[PDB]
Amino acid sequence: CPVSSYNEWDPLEEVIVGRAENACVPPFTIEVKANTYEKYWPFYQKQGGHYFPKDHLKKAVAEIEEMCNILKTEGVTVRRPDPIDWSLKYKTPDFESTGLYSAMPRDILIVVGNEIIEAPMAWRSRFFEYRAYRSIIKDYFHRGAKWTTAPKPTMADELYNQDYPIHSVEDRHKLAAQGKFVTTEFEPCFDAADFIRAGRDIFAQRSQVTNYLGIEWMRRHLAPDYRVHIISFKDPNPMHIDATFNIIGPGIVLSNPDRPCHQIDLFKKAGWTIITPPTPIIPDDHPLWMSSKWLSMNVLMLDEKRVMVDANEVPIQKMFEKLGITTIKVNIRNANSLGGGFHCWTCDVRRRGTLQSYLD
Amino acid sequence: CPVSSYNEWDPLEEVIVGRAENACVPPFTIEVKANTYEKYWPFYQKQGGHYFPKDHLKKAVAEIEEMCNILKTEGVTVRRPDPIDWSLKYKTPDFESTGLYSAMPRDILIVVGNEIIEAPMAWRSRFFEYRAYRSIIKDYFHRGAKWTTAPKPTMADELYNQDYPIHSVEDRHKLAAQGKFVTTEFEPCFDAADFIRAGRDIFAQRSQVTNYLGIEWMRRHLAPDYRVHIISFKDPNPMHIDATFNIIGPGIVLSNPDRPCHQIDLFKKAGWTIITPPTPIIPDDHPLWMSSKWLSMNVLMLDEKRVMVDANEVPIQKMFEKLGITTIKVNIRNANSLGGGFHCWTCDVRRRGTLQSYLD
């Protein structure tokens, strides 16, 4: 029973940590454009199909190796995906593309109980990303874990709004207000990182890569043991929920001040403690090709009282400390450029604990 | 400027490939015993001074001829040592002995920049092994290359620990732990294969045939342009570093799972990718008179994306392929018996590239 995790905070025992090796800039297609900050469009336009800066990747490798050493020191068993060249171009009957990377296990794998679930993904450059984790998953399967792969999409043109106003306009907010994004409801699609666990209740957000059909698939597949709730936030470019609403303990959540939850009162009524972290201090000149500065709150809980947090983000370190939570500081400044913090770079496989309800 | 090579992976242009002709079983002296697996001691005891099985040598000749054809096909210029009868007994004022062979250019020649260096060797049966390569070296010299011969040892009794517990005991590990082997620090000695190149940094291991004095000689001779680092591994019978820690690209290394490096964190901190190859599939009944089954990882890089690998070792072929490295499969099963794989059987003379640092 190697696999067993019901939430984001029980005592961590086993985890999968991604790899920065051979990461490739994804081709600049509509869904990629819908996520890139204008600032990087020229980079994507010129670099697509090529590896991310090798000098930069090398620093990310060292940072993640250190993070793994600390995890082992903290008593956690660490697994790593297989090294793969992400530059290989593949062709399905629906499209052609080069790959991205396997840096973010959280984007593709979610563990609910004793079941490991492979998300379908929504990006053409991430269609074959599961290939890096199969050696690990088959081992868990042989050892008794349940293994599920959500329906892999065709990712044909119909899945995308080829005429999305990506070009800056921000009324994406209105569309967002309507639940209207770059991905249509043509077929189910989702990144696992758009789901966050709190025992019997899982919270999901409809985002640029996770559609209602995808959420309904998760809901139908997990019922009746788990309830999947849809929540929304003031956010014109969502992709993943863990740098917006990160649950760090039973009834305790970190809520991004810039992305307030429309259903916050549901949690206040449940007697939950909503904490708004201080702002990130990461330099504006440091390249964050895939996300926002909010990776600072993308922490990983080793247990209720131990949090792995970024070495450079002192203000948020202080916050945890005043709360009596021990801070394990690790520097992943360069790994951040690939699009993730601690929660994104990992996938908790086994946390010591039981299935409970925290919403009463 | 025929000679010019700074690492193990730049685009290969010229190479020297050894010969299996007239190879002789070396006399069974202490340094030979310290390298032979118990299984072969009777062979060495009865065959010493005689040619290796002629029927076996003939298959090795054919395999290496084919390997040379493929090298030419791959655009590489191939040079071969002069044919010599290795059975001739010679006598220095310090000892008497018959020779071995000139099958392994990597054991005696190392190219650093535009300089070709002849290692001193540490085996009495390899004292005059340089004679097979002089026609080639003089030609390069006439053409402008630098030529260096490290101090040839007397190889008197004082160079050897005549009371080394070779007879199986494995605490050779403790001695090994102390940097204590069959060769003393009486005078400098080394095989060039105990050094592996990565531009401005060269890594060396103190082994059964390479002593600290020998390493210090290389360090002093190459400074200040090159830095020679000493690294060690969990290995009770080292002789050569290329079937233990084979560097295959800038910041990429193949590390033998059975012989972990004590200084691995130095490389993880440099952001290097450490790959552990799958186990060899070579039959236990096939005679490997001079080494271990690990010849499988003793690959030769034609360039960063092309590797010459053994035809029979499918698992490691697959590994390179998932990494996007094209595999050039050649069968050298019988040549393996002489003690080497592709890296050992060759000496890269010219690789298209410049002197760089890869350790930052």
Image: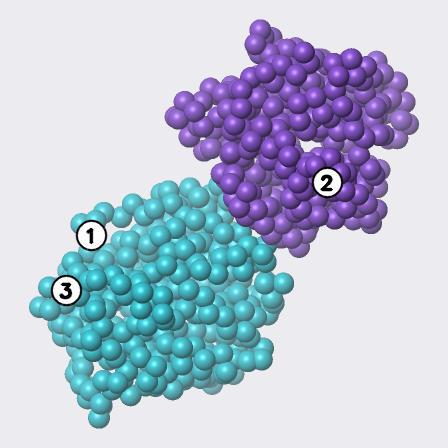
Chain colours: A purple, B cyan
x and y percentages locating residue B309 in the rendered image = 39, 52
Residue, disc 1: B286
**Amino acid type, label 2:** Glu
x and y percentages locating residue B330 in the rendered image = 35, 52
Quarter location, residue B318: top left
Quarter location, residue A263: top right
- Same chain? Circles 1 and 3: yes
**Mark number, residue B41:** 3
Q: CA distance from mark 1 to mark 2?
A: 63 Å
Q: Earlier in the sequence, mark 1 or mark 3?
A: 3
- State which quarter of the image contains the N terminus of chain A: top left
Label 1 Cα neighbours within 10 Å, binned few <14 / some 14-19 / many ≥20: few
x and y percentages locating residue A156 in the rendered image = 66, 20
**Amino acid type, label 3:** Trp
Which of the pair B121/B34 is nearer the observer?
A: B34
- Chain of residue at mark 1: B
Which of the pair A186/B16 is nearer the observer?
A: A186
**Mark number, residue A321:** 2
